[PDB]
Amino acid sequence: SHMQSDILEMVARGWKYFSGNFYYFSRTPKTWYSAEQFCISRKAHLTSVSSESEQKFLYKAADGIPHWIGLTKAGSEGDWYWVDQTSFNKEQSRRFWIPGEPNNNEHCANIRVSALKSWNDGPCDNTFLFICKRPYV
Amino acid sequence: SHMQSDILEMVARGWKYFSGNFYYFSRTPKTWYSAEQFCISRKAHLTSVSSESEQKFLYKAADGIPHWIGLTKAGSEGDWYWVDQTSFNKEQSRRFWIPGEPNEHCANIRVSALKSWNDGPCDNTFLFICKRPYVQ
Ligand SMILES: [Cl-]
Ligand SMILES: [Cl-]
Ligand SMILES: [Cl-]
């Protein structure tokens, strides 16, 4: 009810509700850095992917169009991490990377196929649609 | 004791220490967005400016070279604000904008003078300045 009217407010602002989080699928493309700053300006972050269930929601909604998510590599030689400061599960990510990815500039992940294995490692300065997440509180 | 080794640890990473804060003057240019994400990765933000003495420290060190700072407005129409969420003192700012000033809007320091802030497109590539408070 109060959750229901909060959902209605966010839906009118372009957000989708799923499993206790709000998601913003953008209408225009941005670099990974600019998209993260846009999500911050919306009290959000580029989305993390914490479960197979969340990955399935994201890839279906992304509809085979590249969408930035919030995983980035600390330069070409670092580990991958989530900008929202949840801990990255690199072992499960073997179920999410497109085979052969990360291909290994600056390195940023985007969802680009309508399958479970959908993450691509792409140059962070490419301009793609993007996906913010903000937990419902 | 630990205070001097704390300061020396950041200085050895390439930060300047000035009056209670660490500053990172970058070696490579970036867009404003990429510079802010770099500062975040170092537990920092693009610098705010909250006094005359801080403004003077920054413009002297910037040496007339454009440097991003942490002031922005969302679209040509929002109010200006500091990304580190400190309060923006509009009245004080009038002593820091270049005379005449102020799609994407981001401030950079670009003159070796007190009046040195420029309103520039966020997708320009400039050197930048991070700030991290010293907490003991
Ligand atoms: Cl958008
Ligand atoms: Cl950018
Ligand atoms: Cl640098």
Image (cartoon, coloured by chain):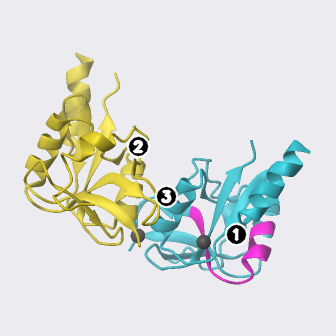
Chain colours: A cyan, B yellow
Q: Residue at x 80, y 67 (%)?
A: A57
Q: Which label belongs to residue A96?
A: 1
Asked if the stretch drawn in magenta spans residue A64, the answer is yes
Q: Which residue is mark 2?
A: B84
Please provide percent x and percent y for residue A65.
Answer: 67, 83
How far across and down, in percent of the image, does residue B33 sit? 40, 63
Residues at marks 3 and 1, CA–CA distance in whole angstroms: 16 Å
Task: Say what amino acid the circle numbered 3 marks.
Answer: Asp
Q: Residue at x 34, y 52 (%)?
A: B71
Q: Which mark is residue A79?
A: 3
Q: Amino acid at mark 1?
A: Phe
Q: In this image, B127 relative to A17: left or right? A: left
Q: Nearer the viewer, residue A58 or A130?
A: A130
As for residue B111 lying within the magenta part, the answer is no
Q: CA distance from mark 3 to mark 2?
A: 26 Å
Boundaries of the magenta span? A57-70
Q: Quadrant of the N terminus of chain A?
A: top right
Marks 3 and 2 share the same chain = no
